[PDB]
Length: 130
Length: 138
Ligand SMILES: O=c1ccn([C@H]2C[C@H](O)[C@@H](COP(=O)(O)O)O2)c(=O)[nH]1
Ligand SMILES: [Mg+2]
Ligand SMILES: [Mg+2]
Image (tube, rainbow over all chains, first blue to last red; front, side):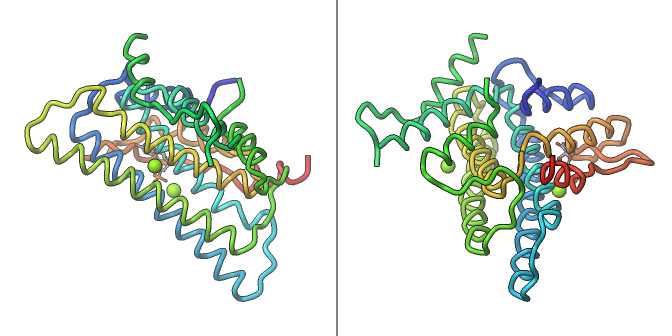
């Protein structure tokens, strides 16, 4: 099965948006777009969390189905976060894997003995060599 | 390999945090916490993008290596966004798959001046309510 990062590549190929094979410095127009899309989805997430909190404050017993709007906006936020990494030519699964390695290993600690923080610059260097 | 959503399940299991198997209405304290985590990482991404744009406005030609902080913050944002879905007991991949299908269906639509893909006539949204009902029973 394809990963959510590979899904963004398929979407950008389908709509003709830049999706370079390896890490590539962006034009400012790209960064501005990614900023706009991230701001929009984080505001929608916030709006749906606020709605759930207001309904709970009024004593509403939320059902699982009540979480669908928030789940949709969280997925949209995932989508535009993956989408930023994809348009930068950066394999999001490789960067996530390194952030997860650090976070998960830190949870074996405070930090454990041979603890090594995330080295995303090292991931970007390896991605440049395909 | 495990998916990134399954990685958050593994992380929450390693720190003893709440991780229901199926969609579970959360306590208000949980919602406020996840909102706080989202805002912290969103602000870091936003600041880093503005930082790169200011360097470009100064005439700097950025390199790929200059992108590593931004890639780090975007991955941090993924981590807390997957984390929110996992603490709600919601399979992020099942929801993402439905969202993704309805985004592929936009391909024939027009484009905004800034590059945003817009929806063609007759487009229909993802049915996330149906994903949630799927996850809740099974
Ligand atoms: O250029 C685009 C336009 C839309 N989306 C995705 C992000 C969300 O999943 C959803 C938001 O689209 P709107 O509902 O705001 O039109 O589509 C992108 O990734 N890139
Ligand atoms: Mg949205
Ligand atoms: Mg961060």
